[PDB]
Length: 165
Ligand SMILES: *[C@@H](C)C1=C(C)C(=O)N[C@@H]1Cc1[nH]c(/C=C2N=C(/C=C3\NC(=O)C(CC)=C3C)C(C)=C\2CCC(=O)O)c(CCC(=O)O)c1C
Image 1 (cartoon, rainbow, N blue to C red):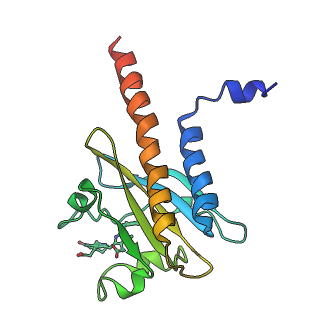
Image 2 (image 1 turned 135 degrees about the vertical axis):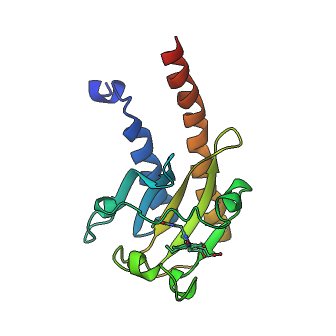
């Protein structure tokens, strides 16, 4: 017994909705969202997860590509970014304006690459208060993101190869 629905589980969103599901439990934060950079430098709305009391940010499509200047390369090397508060970052520039609405008081990012390529990044925002990430929590969370590459690598290839069939 495992519910036919479970066996028929093959939705691309399922595998994605899961990662974030664990992230919340793993990081033990208050809010978490998944975003990637498609061929438009736009934060792809992979999956959005917001704890009770907070609205769904999925209604907000990351307009800021951040592609400008150096940045993508930062993750291309597996750089770790931990900002207790994006408020003390890039002042006098576009940030709080687009970050205030989401009520994101904490910003944590971890690089996720596939076959030496940039796919996306997992972010965890605490809407209740800014928390200092734990050395172990960062590594564990980074592992969760790296895992997605394992699946994507298989599907991304198999899915594409299938069409070439
Ligand atoms: C303002 C939007 C802007 C313009 C215009 C521009 O040309 N550059 C600058 C973009 C920018 N933003 C940061 C800092 C951060 N970026 C992220 C990641 C995101 N971009 C998004 O659109 C979203 C969706 C919510 C995210 C999550 C984050 C988390 C930060 C802050 C944390 C940190 O890195 O400390 C920068 C970096 C500043 C620099 O120039 O070095 C730039 C250029």
